[PDB]
């Protein structure tokens, strides 16, 4: 490794020698975004019946398939509670079948925008990993039990209202509390999904909540494939 | 692997979108800004530039600054990636002695001085102001110490064909944010305008001692450095002929131009953590790069002394200096000096931001007037969180209450606050006065004038001399002491009638005189004074 | 596997066809020029040579120049790949002081000077034209400061057997586009034509200070450097005999030739971003190659001072210099000095290009006359975007209004300009006047002549001497002050009648006289004057 | 700085520098304001051939002859020996202004050559040995070393480290007034060669290369 080679790969990504088009590079960056979640997650989303679309620049519903139709009726879909639909770039249409609309942006350069995509993907496939038939698949119930009050630094996975309600009820194992706040359970799973698969900060989940990391690691090392082939064999 | 272009240790996306260094179980951890769990513990959200190894161009990294793997003498506000760490050392002169060049026990004159760091601006209208140099002016005491000493030239006994020698005690002082380790700078002593008397060149590496920030080199519990006193390898005195002595007695003022040659830089060594002076690094390599890519701000809120800090701002013509984060004026004040907003109002220890005065050079005033034009506002104190800073700006925040001379030193206030400052009496007597005057107000008072008034009203000034105003003394408990006995032959105030009135006057540093007037005027006739004290003779006892 | 012959970092096709440097979110990208998406954002289209490591042959690369990874004191106009970055330092002389070689207190002459960088051109008819070295000619003041000083030789008391010594205060100034870091050049003081009095040689490594562009080495708020006043080891003064003193008193002008030895070059270091003085590089290896492959343009539109830039043009003999991009004259003016086209017309801050006077030397005149003939045009201002530049071209743009001497200094304009420039009268009084004269016009005025016109009309000149025209002053706010009090025994103007006219004249520097004339003329008879100020006596007060 | 016709592979590139003398002043060895004589000169490079028939012509050396002006400048100045006021037991001193000039095709960079001043046939008056590396300046082809807008080099004038004058006794003064001609034999010691460096293109003076190694090989394989 001479000085010339060290300088030559010091500027390996600063010189874009083949650019030639503006919206042809956003497409390559969106493809490189989506190609690093594993194959089993995408195949679970297809066996559920899901769609993913790389639309052009039309933020509010100029998109003809997310057009003036069935839509969100809420106050919170980000990691906070904004939903200012003029300034969104990912939405999921899941009424009769799942369908994900991903606007194309510069995802290799922005890493905060590149996390809402994984958050909505994990929101989409939440109810088929968090449950088996109509339940909470009680490994996940033991997980939320182990993260409820046993760690003050596992409030990165819960909302504010879910935290105060789980504080007030304080013994939530019953099926009364489970079906009253299932959206918060999906929120916790999807937020751990986005923290696990964003490349820059996975170790924040490994540090501040070390047992959710084990759940996600076993998922990635074969639970996704298991639930995929289960839904496949049920599909025939 | 993660991309890291500048090669300091922090990945790019963290440096662009925010990061902080948290301490888990006991180990440290460099994490992105999770707003839920990092805001509770009171951590700071950092931002840097992903293509500079040191965003403020100072010789410490971004990683080293945020994680604490730095020299521990580096000032605490220079632990931020956006505040530069560099030394600003000048020379403090304590007292001088003057004698003729050769029985010389009464043929000398010994006076105390007063040294302050200067920021020489432009002349008003009848002659870009702010430039990079360390200089300070001294102020030899014009008043008397003995009973009847007078007439400096005749006190020393000089004629036209005589030369005088100079000797003084100096002390270096580092008011920057980084320490010097072996080398001391080479100051020169300038009289008048360009008449350089001597160059002080205290020999390097006869010391090995540290000049930390906010500290003196011969520390305050040691003895000062004497100018040309010991003669070990200094066979030359500091000579001064009669003409220069005449200008020195006319002005009673000198100047000490200190240059910027410092030593080496002490850097953290990653194998055993030993901070060791590196012979490769040098401050001469670093200081121009700091001076070209940052925006200085000068402030005198803590006391009436100027403090210079430099904050790393963008520069729109440069592609590498468009990488640094956006710096507003409010954030620069909050991270460099120590301002905070308790309720929503930016204030520096109680004093609100509207009590301070903004001054720029020409370029900055143009640059900021254009921002106020396109922001559609007229008050800079309202939009203080939207004024973007760029590189090579120069701002000067100073206090509104006072009046400043050419060197931006506080030399006087208006009358109303001087009268308000003296409305706390602890004890009153015919021997003196006990008051709680504030420490900043009492820095602009040259001395006092005491007089006695008849019951019908008369004007009898006790100490009717220009060199007899130093009747104030300060005790360490924090309470001043005026004294009538100092120029009344050690005898108290002679009250003739208990229904008399006592009148004490105050003269600020812009109004006092240092030399008698053209004919013989050692009188306090044409001196602008201020009513401070008016009680009766039956109330002081 | 892209081709890169020169190893600067940019691939060949980018360097030939156009490239630009753009900052995204916070990172910098070097991408080719795509016209529709790049012109909107306001970016610059760069073009370079694919076979030189630096197209302008200076020590900074093409990559380092356009991407900002350069020593930050390199001037912003020299960050283009086609503008050379090299220092041009000359010596500025503040004041001289002349004493006789050994009661000598009123036997010295202390005068103010005026130093300007010169560009000596071709002589007219009775003696490559433009030569490349730094030289400046001082001009000693011929007026009087003492009320009754006359006759320099008898002012000092100089005889034919005596010798006279010289002392002066100088300071250096870098007007180029790169800094000098440790070494200062060795200037030499030539008097007359070839009579070198002394060689001013600064001590080696007596400084570690940077000499940045547009900056002085002893800065404007410090003390200047004095020639041989230090004495000690260098007690060798600068001695003139009687004939040389008579030549100096006749001519009142010296010359300071400065050579081109500078220090080393400070280079960016890609690992930790540190700018450090490289002992491997040197300016003397670079300056010939800059001087042989570039085209020089000299321009004085900002102020009446000559400013030299060099632009990398082709040389059709060498195949390595046929690789550089094509450089028209218009683009050279736009990227080197700061001209622009707001509405189609090439102008320099309001002043159109047609107010400037193109002057080439011999070879360039032939080279450009051929292009004008083959373009079938006669007005050069029309085809300014088709005149191709080549290597070793010397062009000299200057302002059309004034008249220039042999060293291309403006020494006095047409009279109609001087009359127009004095049409703003602010204050009229018996003691003086206040006018808003322009900064450019006030460079060429040597002094003023005051006389009184009667109601009939007479002539009585108050300052009727060649060395008494110095009356004018300037307040710093922007208002000059003419003064009749200076040569009227400190008594005001004797308005004998309110129906009189007070005639004031102006004399330019090409019409003034600095010596007594042939027989005895210490009078202003043979001095060409311009009518400036003639109003009634009752509009004055 | 290599001359444009030496860009051909078949034309050699090498420096040919000689000394140009501008004006001389002559005075007696010690009131000397009219006891001097100042004359302008004229220097030309020579190519000394064979004598006609009554005494291979062309050889490798740099030499030039000067021609002191024989005419007058004042109204009635005459008789050089009596103008200076010399007798048989007097010695005179010499001082002049010189300028080097490179008429070859390559530049010299630091070192200047060491010429000698020859009067008559072999009477060497002095050797001019202007101190190397007190300069760092270039002597390009077709250019003078103290350039024409600067001041010339004065022979033995400043005396900084030169305590010896250029003395001349009465007999040599007689031959000088008889001939009004000198000679300046300049040798061929030059500096180093500045070579192109292929990584960054910097032309830099190489301490390995030297003109003394190259010049005999040029002189043996070429045709002048
Ligand atoms: Ca980094
Ligand atoms: Ca960084
Ligand atoms: Ca290239
Ligand atoms: Ca190139």
Image (cartoon, coloured by chain):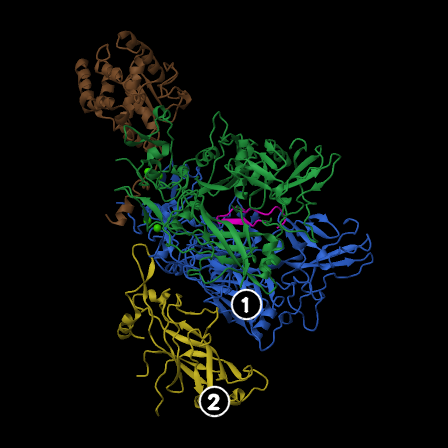
Chain colours: A brown, B green, C blue, D yellow
Q: Is residue B495 above or below residue D128?
A: above
Q: Residue D90 carries which label?
A: 2
Q: In this view, does B504 lie above or below A179?
A: below
Image quadrant in which the N terminus of chain B is located:
top left
Quadrant hosting residue B159: bottom right
Q: Residue B502: x percent and y percent?
A: 68, 36
Left or right for C494, reference A226:
right
Quadrant hosting residue C413: bottom right
Q: Give the range drawn in magenta.
A: B120-141
1 vs 2, front mark: 1
Image quadrant in which the C terminus of chain B is located:
top right
Quadrant hosting residue C320: bottom left
- Label 1 sits on residue: C166
**Label 1: how many residues lie within 10 Å, few (<14), some (14-19) or many (20+)?**
some
Q: Is residue A203 above or below residue B366?
A: above
Q: Element at badge 2?
A: loop
Left or right for C26, reference B518:
left
Q: Which residue lies furthest to the top in this view?
A: A176
B515 or D112, which is in the foreground?
B515
B438 or A172, which is in the foreground?
B438
Ligand 4 is within 8 Å of the C-beta of the residue at disc 2: no
Residue B537 seen from this side: yes
**Label 2: how many residues lie within 10 Å, few (<14), some (14-19) or many (20+)?**
some
Q: Element at badge 1?
A: strand
Q: Are marks 1 and 2 in contact (CB under 8 Å)?
A: no
Q: Residue B303: x percent and y percent?
A: 51, 38
- The residue under the point 34% across, 67% down is D6
Residues behind callouts 1 and 2 on a single chain: no
Q: Residue D186: x percent and y percent?
A: 37, 77
């Amino acid at each position: 490794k001479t000085e010339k080679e060290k300088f030559k790969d010091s500027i390996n990504n600063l010189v874009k020698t083949e650019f030639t088009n503006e919206t042809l590079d956003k497409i390559q960056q969106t493809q490189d975004l989506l190609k690093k979640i594993p194959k089993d997650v995408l195949e679970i989303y297809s066996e559920l019946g899901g769609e993913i679309y790389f639309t052009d620049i039309d933020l509010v519903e100029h998109k003809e398939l997310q057009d003036l139709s069935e839509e969100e009726k809420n106050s919170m879909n980000s990691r906070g509670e904004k939903v200012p639909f003029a300034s969104r770039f990912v939405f999921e249409k899941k009424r009769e079948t799942p369908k994900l609309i991903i606007n194309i942006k510069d995802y290799a350069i922005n890493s905060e925008q590149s996390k809402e995509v994984y958050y909505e993907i994990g929101k989409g496939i939440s109810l088929d990993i968090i449950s088996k038939d109509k339940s909470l698949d009680p490994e996940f119930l033991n997980l939320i039990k182990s993260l409820s009050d046993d760690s003050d630094s596992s409030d990165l996975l819960f909302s504010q209202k879910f935290k105060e309600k789980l504080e007030l009820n304080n013994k939530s194992i019953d099926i009364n509390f489970i079906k009253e706040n299932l959206t918060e359970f999906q929120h916790a799973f999807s937020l751990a999904f986005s923290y696990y698969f964003a490349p820059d900060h996975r170790t924040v989940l490994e540090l501040y909540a070390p047992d959710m990391f084990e759940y996600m690691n076993k998922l990635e090392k074969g639970g996704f494939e298991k639930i995929s082939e289960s839904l496949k064999k049920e599909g025939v | 692997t993660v991309p890291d272009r500048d090669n300091d240790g922090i990945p790019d996306s963290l440096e662009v979108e925010g990061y902080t260094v948290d301490v888990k179980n006991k180990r440290t951890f460099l994490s992105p800004w999770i707003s839920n769990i990092h805001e509770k513990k009171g951590l700071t959200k950092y931002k840097s530039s992903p293509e500079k190894w040191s965003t403020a161009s100072d010789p410490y990294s971004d990683f080293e600054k945020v994680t604490g793997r730095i020299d521990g003498n580096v000032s605490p506000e220079a632990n931020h990636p956006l505040v530069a760490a560099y030394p600003i050392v000048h020379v403090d002169m304590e007292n001088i002695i003057l004698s003729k060049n050769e029985d010389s026990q009464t043929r000398t004159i010994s006076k105390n001085t007063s040294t302050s760091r200067t920021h020489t601006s432009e002349v008003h209208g009848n002659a870009a102001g702010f430039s990079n140099s360390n200089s300070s002016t001294v102020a030899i005491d014009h008043s008397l110490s003995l009973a009847g000493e007078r007439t400096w030239a005749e006190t020393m006994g000089l004629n036209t064909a005589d030369t005088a020698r100079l000797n003084a005690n100096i002390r270096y002082v580092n008011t920057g944010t980084a320490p010097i380790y072996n080398v001391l700078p080479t100051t020169s002593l300038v009289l008048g305008k360009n008449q350089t008397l001597a160059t002080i060149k205290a020999k390097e590496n006869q010391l090995s001692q540290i000049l930390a920030p906010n500290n003196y080199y011969p520390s305050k519990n040691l003895a000062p450095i004497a100018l040309n006193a010991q003669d070990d390898f200094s066979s030359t005195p500091i000579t001064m002929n009669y003409n220069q002595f005449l200008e020195l007695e006319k002005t009673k003022q000198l100047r000490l131009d200190t240059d910027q040659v410092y030593g080496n830089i002490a850097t953290y060594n990653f194998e055993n953590g030993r901070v060791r002076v590196d012979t490769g690094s040098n401050w001469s390599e670093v200081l121009p790069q700091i001076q070209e890519t940052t925006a200085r701000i000068i402030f005198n809120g803590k006391d009436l002394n100027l403090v210079e800090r430099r904050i790393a701002a963008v520069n729109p013509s440069d592609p590498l200096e468009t990488t640094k984060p956006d710096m507003t004026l409010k954030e620069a004040l909050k991270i460099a000096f120590g301002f905070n907003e308790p309720n929503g109002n930016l204030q520096y220890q109680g004093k609100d931001i509207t009590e301070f005065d903004f001054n720029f050079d020409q370029q900055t005033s143009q640059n900021i007037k254009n921002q106020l034009a396109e922001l559609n506002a007229t008050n800079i104190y309202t939009v203080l969180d939207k004024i973007k800073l760029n590189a090579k700006m120069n701002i000067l925040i100073r206090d509104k209450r006072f009046h400043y001379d050419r060197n931006n030193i506080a030399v006087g206030a208006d009358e109303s606050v001087v009268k308000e400052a003296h409305r706390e009496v602890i004890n009153s007597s015919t021997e003196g006065l006990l008051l709680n005057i504030d420490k900043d107000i009492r820095k602009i008072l040259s001395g006092y004038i005491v007089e006695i008034e008849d019951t019908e009203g008369l004007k009898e000034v006790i100490n009717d001399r220009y060199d007899m105003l130093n009747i104030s003394s300060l005790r360490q408990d924090g309470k001043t002491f005026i004294d009538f006995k100092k120029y009344n032959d050690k005898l108290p105030l002679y009250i003739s009638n208990p229904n008399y009135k006592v009148n004490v006057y105050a003269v600020t540093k812009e109004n006092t005189i240092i030399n008698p007037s053209e004919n013989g005027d050692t009188s306090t006739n044409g001196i602008k004074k201020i009513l401070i004290f008016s009680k009766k003779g039956y109330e002081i006892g």
